[PDB]
Amino acid sequence: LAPLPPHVPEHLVFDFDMYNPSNLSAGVQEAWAVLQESNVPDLVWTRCNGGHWIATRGQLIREAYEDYRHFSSECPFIPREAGEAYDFIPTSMDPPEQRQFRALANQVVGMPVVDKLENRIQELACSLIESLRPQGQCNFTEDYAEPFPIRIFMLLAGLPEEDIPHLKYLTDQMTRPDGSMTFAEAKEALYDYLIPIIEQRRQKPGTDAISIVANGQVNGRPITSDEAKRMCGLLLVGGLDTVVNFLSFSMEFLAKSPEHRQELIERPERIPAACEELLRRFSLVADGRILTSDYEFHGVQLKKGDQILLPQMLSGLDERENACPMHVDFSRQKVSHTTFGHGSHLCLGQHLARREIIVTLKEWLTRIPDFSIAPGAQIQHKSGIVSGVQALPLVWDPATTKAV
Ligand code: HEM
Ligand SMILES: CN(C)c1cccc2c(S(=O)(=O)NCCCCNC(=O)[C@]34C[C@H]5C[C@H](C[C@H](C5)C3)C4)cccc12
Image 1 (cartoon, rainbow, N blue to C red):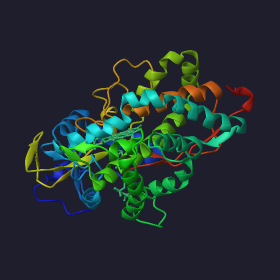
Image 2 (cartoon, helix red, strand yellow):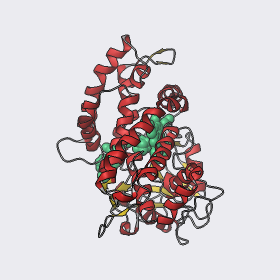
Image 3 (cartoon, rainbow, N blue to C red):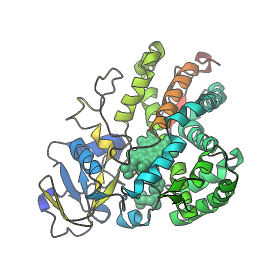
Image 4 (spheres, protein in one colour):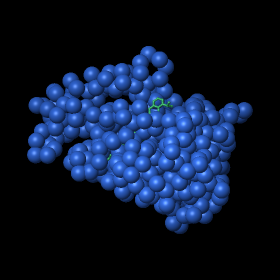
């Protein structure tokens, strides 16, 4: 624990550890929910991980994300050293600078692009599932959750499939380091990989994501190689960790709820609604901002330079905006959440993600309508900037499956 700063009131202290919260064994969402019990203030200070603020209610979380003037993305991660080193684009920029870079990225992952890659998305899902179907078992996270999104990125970025193993490796070191290299090294390794492709597509442009970004213009002038690699880095990692883990949370729930499986099988038209409800219940991201100056927020004095965690995960779990928040109801009428963020940085891949989720639910239940958690298995969760599932062993009787 770090020594409490003089300007911080002792009665607002609540030492929550975002990387190792208590009661994690009861579920990661449930663990963060402790920040929402009646005896916990709307805004608290934890002495963990260097010391920082934490907004615990949807109201404050949304407000801080809207106000970039006071809450800057220049240092969006906790601990400070990590946020300071972070330089991906446009996640580490504030408007107006961010505006142009965000518009360019929107061109490679926006809705229009989704509708065009869908055949490959649906095709990829079916291929992956059919290959597992006969087995009667699988480790969902390793066998589907991971391969699905990374193959989608290779397609949109126009990269060859033989590069997946190496990219998977580099991305794994940027969140699950084995020791071979430290973030910075993996980043450079990634940049080393991207720079050549970028320079080459500058003169020989294709219709892929890299081509578009490489030939982009900002501030009336051509984007630099430095800016291009920093944007491409995000385009790669942005849709991995999030999708892999979200799909895992979703499948873990369905594996433990036969009635919900049956609901979607009998009422397929409800899958898009089911997707939104799962996004609320199993929200998983939590990054933050840094104070640009001294500022009084909701009766609390914030000091310039202070870091504040604004858990996107917590908004939809706030009992003040969603009744019985831990209950999953595909018929819930006013599903509110900030799972994809809020404000100027609202997730650009949100449309792609939903398509990935919906296609997955539809194609999996079509071929493997009945499945369960492997007997004796005890699912483990992990907590951080992007919380998730360690592994998810599933089992089923092939006799109940169907090839389509
Ligand atoms: C279940 C999946 C997803 C979730 C929960 C999610 C979540 C988020 C969140 C919360 C942010 C904003 C962070 C902040 O304000 O600092 C964001 C940003 C972003 N996401 Fe996603 N994401 C998902 C998938 C995707 C996908 C599929 C990609 C595509 C490569 C992607 C690309 C981006 C990009 C480009 C941004 C930065 C936008 C900006 O700074 O202007 N995301 N995402
Ligand atoms: C557990 N502790 C100690 C850590 C271990 C290893 C790396 C860490 C890092 S790190 O080096 O910055 N690595 C992780 C983050 C890099 C990849 N992800 C992204 O940019 C984001 C940017 C947006 C917000 C979320 C979700 C998605 C969009 C992708 C994160 C930060 C904080 C703690 C870390």
